[PDB]
Amino acid sequence: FDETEIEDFKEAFTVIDQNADGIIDKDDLRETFAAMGRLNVKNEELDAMIKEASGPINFTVFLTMFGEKLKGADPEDVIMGAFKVLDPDGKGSIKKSFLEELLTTGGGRFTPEEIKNMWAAFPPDVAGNVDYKNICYVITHGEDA
Amino acid sequence: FDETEIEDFKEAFTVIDQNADGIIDKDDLRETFAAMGRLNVKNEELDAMIKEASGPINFTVFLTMFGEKLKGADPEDVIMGAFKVLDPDGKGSIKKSFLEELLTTGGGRFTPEEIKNMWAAFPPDVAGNVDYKNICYVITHGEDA
Amino acid sequence: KLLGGGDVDHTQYAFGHTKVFFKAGLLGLLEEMRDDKLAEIITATQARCRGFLMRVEYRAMVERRESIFCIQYNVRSFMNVKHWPWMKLFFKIKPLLK
Amino acid sequence: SKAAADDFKEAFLLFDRTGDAKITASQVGDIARALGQNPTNAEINKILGNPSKEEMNAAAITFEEFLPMLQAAANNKDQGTFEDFVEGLRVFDKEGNGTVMGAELRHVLATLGEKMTEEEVEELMKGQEDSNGCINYEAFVKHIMSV
Amino acid sequence: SKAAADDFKEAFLLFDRTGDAKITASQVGDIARALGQNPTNAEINKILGNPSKEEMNAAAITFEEFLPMLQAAANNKDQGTFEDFVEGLRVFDKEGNGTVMGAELRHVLATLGEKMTEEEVEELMKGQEDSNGCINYEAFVKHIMSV
């Protein structure tokens, strides 16, 4: 965890903790979702978020919960560092079959089935290994941009 | 030491001395590191910083310790002064082989092996002697920007 | 340029303006001996190369060691997270920030 | 002999991916090179077949066969003379300066004799050949014999 | 003599790159020039060989040989007469004004007698020759004798 990433989680903690007392309760979760447009947010969704913690969601409990789910989270500059080492001549997005062979043949984390799941929402270019960069974006901030 | 550089070290001394009494003790070092995100900062790192001084870290002991480690520290405007004299026509980053030849053939501080270490984290452009300016940045403030 | 390769007697032939000249069956014999002599010379020079070739692969494999992991773990996160309320939230919200 | 070098057995535990203390016959070529031996691939191939050992079918190994094969390859290290390596490349390009044109060394290392992949050829020229397209083989063969 | 000039020993510590207080025989020509002596390179060469000293093989030095070689070169400073330097270049170009055409002095300084590199020839004309292509050697030889 770099310090600017921890400051981003402190700003997200303050936007969900609308009572500003330092502990995100279930009313803060529901009023942050209603301010984003969720008028139908069920109480069972709020209870499942609180069921991931053993205590009240203060800043260090929110940081330890996000730490334990993001144990391989990598910032965009280090993902582009590794992709610039895979394309060491610069500019070009690397081939689809080169990333499939190098993921498998180096590591067990690069096994195929997982490579079909990589191509599956990370579209073609991304999946193929040709573009580059959009995948670093969606690994640090999810969903389609 | 120019006076604005000494005021920058006075501001860094006040941010690490969180008790504001004028002497940075080991608790100030640990609480400044914990406020930057270092939850695992060992006591042996704090003891190795205090082992570089012969007494308590007040403002003049911190200035003399930084003076004795930075006996060739050069501000960015004087490094760009010297690089504008090496590129006297302006704008262009100077060639890789020109900086290797002129470092060696003028001085013993510009010997090759050291030139391979210059290219080694100061990347290509920087190492090569083509870009310019990013090396002045990282000599006044380290690590990748 | 072609004759560059082969474990052949580089003697036995000779070039000129319109064509190459070649021995048989003596010069033919010569070359042959020669041929064997390069396998030696060659075969040995190949090896080191081969050897050496892979020796650089290890230096790369090794470097790579971590950059992968980084990549490895890093992805996994996301696959888990991207479905998490809190994380989607942070997401829509991450922009309003400065 | 021990000089009993027990670090050859510790390096066999770094190349065996299953942890059972056996190394397949296809890895023995590259691990002899990683222990400080450069047998040519035809030599590694011959010896194998010589001993009615087929590298075409599944293989396992034991340390008790890999140790004497490394000791049979260790006598052939007297073939590694650097005079003949630099004189080979000195006969490969004209003029009195040691420079191969880029693509001459890349196509010769991939297609002449024991085929080296073009991926390995690019990894062996990376850094020693600059953008002039001229590989200085005095420093190139020096750095190739540094590993 | 000391006048014991101990700054010659302090300048030997600025030219010895290893710090062991020895200066190789190939540096002795340029360091005699940096101590205020201009022996020609053939003279530096002869003296060396004269003393069965080979500048072809590795060399070291000691201060105890470099001091008397600088004192043997110091008698030859009576050959540095500026009348003959300005009259040499005055016979090298027509008319009553001291100007050499640029390329005449550059090709003569690189190819006639003791070969000066064209890099050093450009560094000695830089500033004294303007864009008219005419080197005024009255001020040019004045500035060359200012160092």
Image (cartoon, coloured by chain):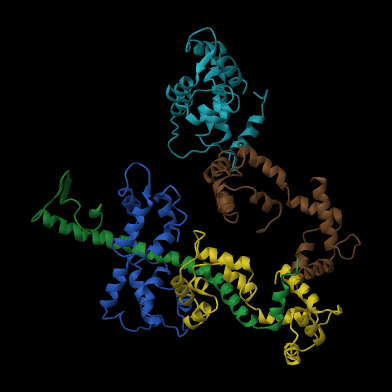
Chain colours: A yellow, B brown, C green, D blue, E cyan
Which one is in front, D48 or A120?
A120
Does residue A141 appear to the left or right of A23 in the view shown? Answer: left
Q: Residue furthest bottom?
A: A44
| Residue at left offset 57%, top offset 43% | B94
Q: Is residue A73 above or below residue B13?
A: below
| Residue at left offset 78%, top offset 72% | A11
Q: Where does the C terminus of chain A fall, quadrant-wise?
A: bottom right
| Residue at left offset 82%, top offset 50% | B6
Q: Position of residue E66 (x, y in %)?
A: 56, 31
Which one is in front, E27 or B42?
B42
Q: Is residue B19 visible?
A: yes
| Residue at left offset 80%, top offset 45% | B2
Q: Is residue B90 above or below residue D112?
A: above
Q: Is residue B41 visible?
A: no
Instruction: Choose top left, top right, bottom left or bottom right for residue B51.
Output: bottom right
Q: Position of residue D83 (x, y in %)?
A: 34, 52
Does residue C1 appear to the left or right of A104 in the view shown? Answer: left
Q: Where does the N terminus of chain A fall, quadrant-wise?
A: bottom right
Q: Position of residue D70 (x, y in %)?
A: 37, 73
Q: Position of residue E38 (x, y in %)?
A: 55, 22
